[PDB]
View (cartoon, protein in one colour):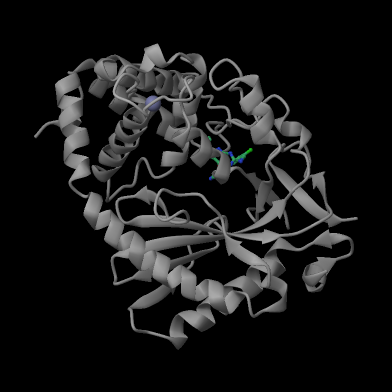
Length: 348
Ligand SMILES: CCCc1cc(=O)n2nc(NCc3cc(-c4ccncc4)ccc3Cl)nc2[nH]1
Ligand SMILES: [Zn+2]
């Protein structure tokens, strides 16, 4: 019941000071890397993007894995969609990145190739810390570093565009009944970001918007600022991420749930905030019912084989192109069992 979930949340708090130390280790390495990068002409205007709850730039993703985004101010960007994918684009210009231009197009692989070299150079140069360097399979996390042989950080290069959001997002960010039309208009005036994921295509990124709507998450502007308005939205997201983490830990050898990530969990959770816009639907005292709402919607997404991207609704995260049908059935079976029996996975 709800007291079992509160105990899970209390136990997760116990690792708060360990996560803070690990994040501080990441911050020191990133800040060193930021210094060098600003010496290269192509990356002269690089800075850290405000995406996480540690300082402002280190984003927790899993127990000992962090995410960091370097933003690059790039003006006069023109986008051309790569064939009805809605998510992927070529980058044009109507400048420092001239070396990576092939025709009128900006090569993500050439820009990404130099980025890696500089970081790989500077990782070796100064070692008052044990820092190594991996290449994760997908190029969306551009570089992965391993600090003290425990902490891993994904570093992502992103182009910053101050232009109006692409037309594929016109029907996304469906927050009007929850956070208001005024807030939706404000958010869409902010920049958007382009990260090199696979041709030489770029994918849109809204990491800065996720942080904003997580930390300013109520219908009431004073949600969670006083004892009378304590909701459980953040705790429900934490429990959902931890549920997936704990289930994945049971299949270390086979990696049966390898295709599922906290990105999927977060997407479903923000759809549930859309569906349940009132702060009274997230009363802290209703933790058990609210968590059930989140789990039940996730199950529905698994069974209908459909999880819409929060910003580009025509992009289905759960299409069989991306996640095998049998993988979705397997996770459906695991979660359905956990829900029907009060989440034994959380038992001590
Ligand atoms: C606030 C809700 C969660 C969220 C945060 C965020 O920063 N973003 N950024 C986009 N961009 C659009 C997009 C992203 C991905 C993706 C695939 C894999 N890892 C990352 C992103 C795949 C397809 C598409 Cl269309 N969506 C989101 N959702
Ligand atoms: Zn709140």
